[PDB]
Image (cartoon, rainbow, N blue to C red; front, side, top):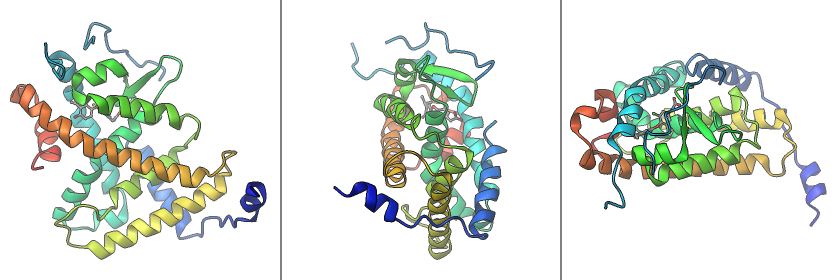
Length: 253
Ligand SMILES: CC(C)c1cc(Oc2c(Cl)cc(CC(=O)O)cc2Cl)ccc1O
């Protein structure tokens, strides 16, 4: 026990004005690159749940038509982060390929609406778990909805979502990177700045930070699992339906 005491005995350092700068740049890089009022729903006849793993081409088409902008927004987000913009093109590619699905999934998960039990892709199209699943994501769809439901309680604000994206972007998990050190350092700086921003928000939730950190694992699973679905998508879907950017970002794996 002694949880209440231990909790209160913990030091909650606020953000140092080095971290407040990061937290501001990042927060705006995020806000300016991610756009519920006039959100159009995706027709219930599209992707309505033989072949246990068949991909509904119609649904798939609807999602690939809006994926290029979604991917462009993540790239735009990265470009607005100093420590990223200064990296070699090759590095930016590897980083982007390594976190694009995660960030896109995070943005989808936070736009989750419990009322309608849907997600809003590109901040406009509202999709039901079934549709996104038949459209190609399969279980990954189940995973993003599961994450979206659980993130409602966290009340993440633009900054937490923003730093969470920076943390995902600045990873040295993939190979072929050049500036491993500089990225590593940006990672640690964002994590630290992120943690202090969470101390500042004072969430009425027990072990919030540790829990929010576990969401990163959820997103990386979604990311990794997405690479599989993508392969399955290339098998089951006409190549003409795959936009160029979509292919560059998820192929070669
Ligand atoms: C079906 C297939 C084309 C596919 C859909 C897919 O759906 C999403 C889309 Cl379009 C856009 C976003 C992010 C956003 O809301 O901007 C987030 C998500 Cl999860 C992600 C990866 C994929 O390979």
